């Protein structure tokens, strides 16, 4: 139980005589405006503040805000500056705490650096009543828990107006945006599953997968290892071919075009939605620059340079930042190197001959992801440290700049293994004549049997699927870190902002639009993550957290630029994934230039290249030839080269240049047309809606001609 | 001589009784506000209007505008709504005519459709005094002629403030923008001439031009005609090789990168410049939509549909518009076809044997350009007609939409021959085994001897150089169409807007940034056109034209979007001009893959392909073999194919695929990096300047704290 107050205060009861000395200076300044009262309880005492009327419209008229009017045309109230209710119970606790907090910022000797100084420990508004409990008299928070934050009701809409009224415009703006994201993922997921099912239908009626799964060929490949690997049948490893056609379907290209156009129309939908929201709440964009106090070490260094009586050191630490990005890349690839080398060439010790080499990939990805998740906090801390060194101007500039520097780091270490696997995997190894040795002592890396697409898909799928669960489970074992009202809310967690909360969503959006070329069904997994995530966040904002202060923002700001950036980067990278990785272009080239008939047959016989086994470099031979055939005289590998019985052997063939030319041509055409379409749907859909335009115009007319009297 | 009036009126003295009947209705409405007086003179009488004071600040306070204040902080006067001069001679004739014109628009029974109706013939403000003349008492127009509009003083700066004060914000905005364009062309031209001179230096020290100009080879090419052409020496046509190296220099690539970055920094410079101009004149962007009356056939069709008691027919005529664009393309190429066929295979008749075939190209381009310039007015008239059929909403929407539809047409017919020559010229012809016949009766077109770059350069150079002169000279032979003050100004030309005046500048900007890949030195020619053009336009606005009405705009609007569009389109098209046309990539491929040494030699011996002359299709042989050599057994052509003594003959060789792959790879890399750099310099340079920001902030502070008293 309490009376009707606004903002709390947590002092620390017992240098320290300076803490208690200066501690009473601030409330003497607070006698002038607010009516404060304090109390004594169990362990450490607290200070209380209550607003009185005759200064509250003084501060409410200090700034221009809108409140509901007296008149109402066409079944809806209108808004104006400050008049025509007169109840003395119409100021919401959100608004009351907002005004009180503005008085807290305005006077100083600010309370922010005073709070971080050590004299005060916390400064937070309280909430009315309690979530759930017994016999509460219709709490608003209880209503919000009963309608929004429970797992039982997930499929019903966001009650966005109530959450705006109770938590403020920023939090409500976040949940509104995530609502729009999850709502836009529905047709993306449905079309995703349609494309995957069309992949499932045409499995047993294609040419390449039959020709790989066929018996009676006795065709043998080159050993793909240095020492301890033998020759192997094409018909042996044929599951990966079946799933390969399940993923590189000629409908998946259509799905990629659909996804780029989907990202663009998502941007349009959200611009339109925040436009109508900024109608419904506040539209006056004349927010005062320089109003808030500056970041205090700029004042401290201004005292230093003021004693001395630079714009170069920031550029120097920007170069330091780029250095950090580069070794973030190469350290990422090093970590993938170690993870692939979790268990290499271990066949000599057990002699049990399992040699399945499938779960090895799974351990590589899992151990890999543990290293990413552990490294991520480190990169965040380096970001805060470096940005702290930079000494920016204000609070807003500090938050913006820190946001950017955090995002680059999480982008890099979160997407570098997928870039390594999708592109640079099995390209740089030579012919069986001469292998490319790294560290000048052993071979680089061979591809997966039948294509390096499977590692991409099962690696991608459990990052996007399981990153959250591995993060939540492992994060706690790692040591990461009649009752009175303020004593309840003191024991809650503090509030830290929304940047660690937006960040995961932007990266997830990356996993959607950056790799749906080789792997469809991705918006499905993002949706299944998303439904659980939104309600988990709601339960976090109600249960485990104290109230925020509700600073009134008008748009999310930087995150829209980051989304537009990722959504524009998507196109070129999907072009390279379709052309290079997906093995789609050699099928079309073989269907148009080397057909020998109408349709394709012997595509696999076209790709392979017939090495002569007598030409290894004295020790790169297989150790024990397995002799599945009686003997073996020639092995085959897939690199488009000429057979050895021609006068030139092992050189770069004609077909390599032909297929390379076709691949690059597809990159040009795809990138240009999809840039044009994505710019087109930007141009077509109006950023402003009609209803808001004519509705604010009608409101302006009725306000003026009702106002002149 | 006159007294001090503002706006004239031209009636038509003698159905007609309705003209004189309704003609007196408007001045009876004008008795209420303005003091009008009329006169009688020579041929057809006129009506005069003079403003009086006590209604003039009524209308000046009807709208918010800024006028100079009384106070001045830091050596500069400030501005505010309307107060604190009080002279009754401080309203400029521009402003007085502006207010009078607003009263002319506001009351109706509008004067615009009344003017186009037939009752009134003209309605124009007059000017003070006269340009030049004898013993004038310091005319402002005389000052402007003496300082700005004369050819004698061209190199001195634009007096932009005076022209804003005397002609208004729109005209001054035009001349300001063109000033920025011409000023930005200086370093572009200097770097252009540096690149051309670097081309001039390295002529006699290269490999390919020596190898073409060399004697002692006796190498012969295939005849390049159907019947009446013989075999020819490579050393014969060697001027075109020399100039070819003069144009496809490996420094010209650097110049192309410089030009894309130049276009982007031009956009930044002009955004910044109109920002400071909109500081100096008017910054309140809250201009009233729907204030002006609507376009009258929308009211007429609203009367029709109002009797009946569509949004599809506009889409249908948009499809009609796209049809018009397509046959504008193909008609353009047809016209080039005719112009190339101005004199074809005429060698049979004279038997004089000149056969120079150089001036033939010149006649093709000249006749071509006559056809473009004659066709251009037709396309303009179709644009006005079609847009008239569309029936838009307002005047502003009509001007915008007509602007767009005019620009597409002039873009298409102005750039289609250069697109045909640069790309599609000599690509589609086959090998000497089988030629590609168009119309199924005769051959398509061969390339120019030694490269199709010369036709591009000499065709481009005289369009951009001579289009203006041919337009001005031919345009007049084609029949294209004590004295009192208003009788002087009646005999002047009317005013038609700025769209035919912006249009030539945007197309010229196209000729700069769209084809500096194969042809440097282009900003030089644009500069030489430009200096003459700006002063010719100034002399036009002073001498041959009556005054405009000075509608206050705040930016050029649509033309900035068109400039950004062209400047963004420049990159991809420069990539294709460098890669495909410019013959730069085969030099690099030969320098890296078929070197046989360090540097290049025998590049020409590498390119040619050795056809066997015994394999023509019974009549495609040369008619009379010229027999410059005793006999001839093999001819050579440049198409990357295999010699006939191999088991495969005349097929597509390896080198064709290799060079094609290299070309497309260059297109990808160039387009992406130059998009990134052009986006980068957009991001770096601040769109807002510092001085304007802090200066308007200081003005706001001083205005408020000076205002509270």
Image: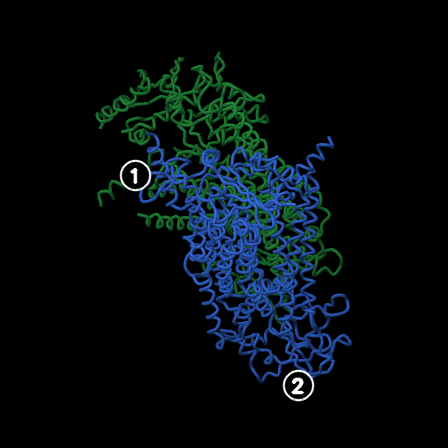
Chain colours: A green, B blue
**Label annotation for residue A297:** 1
**Label annotation for residue B628:** 2
Tag 1 subunit: A
Report x, y in % for residue A210: 71, 51
Picture residue at 39% right of the left edge, 48% below the top: A321
Q: Is residue B233 visible?
A: yes
Circle 2: element type: loop
Spatial CA distance of label 2 from label 1 is 88 Å
- Characterize the local packing of mark 1: few (<14), some (14-19) or many (20 or more) Cα atoms within 10 angstroms: some
**Label annotation for residue A45:** none
Residue B63 or residue A516, whichever sits in front: B63
Q: Is residue A634 visible?
A: no
Tag 2 subunit: B
Q: Is residue A534 left or right of residue B230?
A: left
Report x, y in % for residue B657: 62, 65
Residue A21 or residue A433, whichever sits in front: A21
Residue A298 or residue B663, whichever sits in front: A298
């Amino acid at each position: 139980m309490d009376y009707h107050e606004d903002d709390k205060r947590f002092r620390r009861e017992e240098l320290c005589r300076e803490a208690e000395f200066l501690k009473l200076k601030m409330p003497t300044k607070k006698v002038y405006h607010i009516s404060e009262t304090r109390g004594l309880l169990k362990t450490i005492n607290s200070v209380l503040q209550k607003i009185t009327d005759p200064i509250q419209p003084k501060v409410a008229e200090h700034r221009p805000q809108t409140t509901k009017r007296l008149s109402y045309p066409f079944s809806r109230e209108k808004q104006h500056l400050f008049d025509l209710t007169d109840r003395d119970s119409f100021f919401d606790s959100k608004t009351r705490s907002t005004i009180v907090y503005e008085i807290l910022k305005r006077t100083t000797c600010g309370i922010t650096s005073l709070l971080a100084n050590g004299v005060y420990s916390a400064a937070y508004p309280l909430h009315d009543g309690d979530y759930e409990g017994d016999n509460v008299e219709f709490n608003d928070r209880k209503l919000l828990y009963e309608e929004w934050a429970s797992y039982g009701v997930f499929y019903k809409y966001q009650p966005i107006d109530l959450v705006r009224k109770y938590f403020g415009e920023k939090v409500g703006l976040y949940f509104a945006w995530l609502g729009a994201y999850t709502q836009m993922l529905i047709p993306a997921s449905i079309v995703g599953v349609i494309v995957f099912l069309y992949g499932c239908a045409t499995v047993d009626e294609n040419i390449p997968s039959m020709e790989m799964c066929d018996q009676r060929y006795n065709i043998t490949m080159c050993p793909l290892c240095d020492k301890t690997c033998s020759y192997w049948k094409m018909s042996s490893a044929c599951a990966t071919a079946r799933a390969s056609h399940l993923f590189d379907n000629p409908a998946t290209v259509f799905f990629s075009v659909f996804m780029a156009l989907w990202a663009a129309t998502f941007m349009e939908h959200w611009k339109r939605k925040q436009m109508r929201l900024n109608y419904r709440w506040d539209l006056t964009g004349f927010e005062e620059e320089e109003e808030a106090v500056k970041d205090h070490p700029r004042a401290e260094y201004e005292a230093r340079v003021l004693e001395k009586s630079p714009a170069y050191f920031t550029n120097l630490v920007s170069i330091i930042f780029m250095i950090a990005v580069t070794f973030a890349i190469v350290l990422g690839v090093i970590i993938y190197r170690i993870s692939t080398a979790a268990a290499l060439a271990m066949n000599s010790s057990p002699s049990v001959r399992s040699n399945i080499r499938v779960t090895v990939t799974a351990t590589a990805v899992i151990i890999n992801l543990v290293v990413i998740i552990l490294l991520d906090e480190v990169y965040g801390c380096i970001a805060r440290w470096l940005t702290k060194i930079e000494v920016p101007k204000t609070e807003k500039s500090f938050e913006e700049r820190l946001t950017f520097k955090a995002f680059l780091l999480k982008f890099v270490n979160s997407y570098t293994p997928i870039f390594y696997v999708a592109f640079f995997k099995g390209r740089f190894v030579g012919r069986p004549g001469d292998y490319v040795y790294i560290f000048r002592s052993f071979r680089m890396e061979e591809c997966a049997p039948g294509g390096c697409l499977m590692e991409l898909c099962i690696q991608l799928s459990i990052i996007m699927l399981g990153k959250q669960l591995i993060q939540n489970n492992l994060f706690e074992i790692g040591i990461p870190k009649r009752k009175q009202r303020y004593e309840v809310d003191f024991n809650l967690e503090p509030f830290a902002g929304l940047t660690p909360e937006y960040m995961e969503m932007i990266i997830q959006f990356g996993f959607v639009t950056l790799f749906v070329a080789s792997f469809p069904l991705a918006p499905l997994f993002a949706l299944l993550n998303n439904i659980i995530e939104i309600r988990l966040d709601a339960k976090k904002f109600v249960t485990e957290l104290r109230r925020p202060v509700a600073i009134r923002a008008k748009d999310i700001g930087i995150w829209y630029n980051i989304l537009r950036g990722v959504g524009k980067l998507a196109v070129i990278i999907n072009a390279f994934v379709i052309s290079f990785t997906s093995d789609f272009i050699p099928r079309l080239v073989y269907l148009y230039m080397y057909s020998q008939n109408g349709t394709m047959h012997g595509f696999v016989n076209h790709t392979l290249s017939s090495f002569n086994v007598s030409d290894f470099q004295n020790g790169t031979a297989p150790n024990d030839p397995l002799d599945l055939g009686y003997e073996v005289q020639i092995c085959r590998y897939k690199d488009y080269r000429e057979p050895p019985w021609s006068e030139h052997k092992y050189d770069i063939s004609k077909d390599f240049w032909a297929v390379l030319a076709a691949r690059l041509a597809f990159v040009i055409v795809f990138q240009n047309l999809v840039m044009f379409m994505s710019d087109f749907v930007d141009w077509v859909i109006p950023d402003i809606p009609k209803d808001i335009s004519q509705q604010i115009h009608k409101e302006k007319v009725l306000m003026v001609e009702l106002f002149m009297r």
